[PDB]
Amino acid sequence: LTEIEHLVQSVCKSYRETCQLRLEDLLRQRSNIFSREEVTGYQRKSMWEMWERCAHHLTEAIQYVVEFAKRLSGFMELCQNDQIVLLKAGAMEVVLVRMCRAYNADNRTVFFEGKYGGMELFRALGCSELISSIFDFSHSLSALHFSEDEIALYTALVLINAHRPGLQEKRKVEQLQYNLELAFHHHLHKTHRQSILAKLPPKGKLRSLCSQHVERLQIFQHLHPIVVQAAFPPLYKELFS
Ligand SMILES: O=C(O)c1ccc(/N=C/c2c(-c3c(Cl)cccc3C(F)(F)F)noc2-c2cc[nH]c2)cc1
Ligand SMILES: CC(C)=CCC[C@@H](C)[C@H]1CC[C@H]2[C@@H]3CC=C4C[C@@H](O)CC[C@]4(C)[C@H]3CC[C@]12C
């Protein structure tokens, strides 16, 4: 039996250990929705308190993605420069993809601080167009009904992309990429799920949305710096200043 069957198992294990929120929990909690009063309470919070809360949650989400990457076979054998290039370009893209598990398309709500709420929860941030675009992206992804292994293999490939500008050992990233592509396509064939391939997001769209999102987080961080629970100095240094 294949190195490729083992790679599937190892990527899904890494995802299971780092997925942050369990899918059964997220699905069971869908009926737990913020009340009108609770939504108004969030809308009345300071922009800067909502930013502190959201920035903290997003930092934590990024760190789970870093831990996911560190567990992908061969990722720790890449040189540090390339590790950082890959994580800088792709970790927030993965966070945006992971969001769809916590998104309920029936009422367009996301799981946030223990209950589901719509995008109006975030009104104090004054980012309605960007936040609407983030909700719209999860709405599009939710139509695929991604399984846990599909999310694991797809987000591994979001990260392990040999086309990212600035890699120093491109051939070594290509080797991991090809094996992950084969793992993903083998798994979709085995589960009769190859039809999702044509429905995956155009790559330019995830990159565009992520670039706009990170640009806004950078603006907030310039205006109102946050305390970061920093665990990854080389990555922190690339993003914070
Ligand atoms: O533990 C560590 O060391 C560490 C290091 C870095 C981290 N995240 C950096 C962020 C942020 C971001 C966030 Cl999440 C919140 C507030 C402000 C920002 C800002 F934009 F300012 F950077 N946004 O995208 C990334 C990113 C993109 C690719 N890779 C990381 C998180 C933990
Ligand atoms: C534009 C701006 C200033 C903020 C974005 C507002 C909002 C869209 C952000 C704030 C917190 C985020 C969640 C945080 C954690 C997770 C868990 C992860 O496993 C999956 C992703 C998820 C649920 C994040 C989704 C995006 C949220 C709600």
Image (cartoon, rainbow, N blue to C red):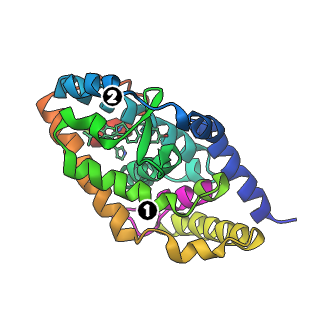
Q: Per the image, is 64 magenta?
A: no
Q: How many marks?
A: 2
Identify the disc placed on residue 36.
2
User: 229 or 85: which is nearer to us?
Assistant: 229
In the image, is the residue at mark 2 within 8 Å of ligand 2 by its beta carbon?
no
Residue 137: percent from left, percent from top:
38, 58
Residue 192: percent from left, percent from top:
73, 73
Question: Farthest residue toward the front?
Answer: 36
Residue 193: percent from left, percent from top:
67, 71
Determine whether 204 is above or below 224 in the image.
Answer: below
User: 149 or 28: which is nearer to us?
Assistant: 28
Q: Quadrant of residue 37?
A: top left
Tell me if 211 is positioned left or right of 71 in this view: left
Q: Quadrant of the N terminus?
A: bottom right
* Mark 2, secondary structure of its residue: helix
Q: Give the label, 1 or 2, closer to the camera.
A: 2
- Magenta stretch: give its range: 152-169
Residue 229: percent from left, percent from top:
38, 24
Q: Amino acid at mark 2?
A: Arg
Q: Earlier in the sequence, mark 1 or mark 2?
A: 2
Q: Is residue 147 visible?
A: yes
Ligand 2 image-quadrant field: top left
Q: Is residue 241 visible?
A: no
Tell me if 166 is positioned left or right of 160 in this view: left
User: 53 or 230: which is nearer to us?
Assistant: 53
Residue pointed to by mark 1:
140
Determine whether 135 is above or below 117 in the image.
Answer: below
Q: Per the image, is 164 magenta?
A: yes
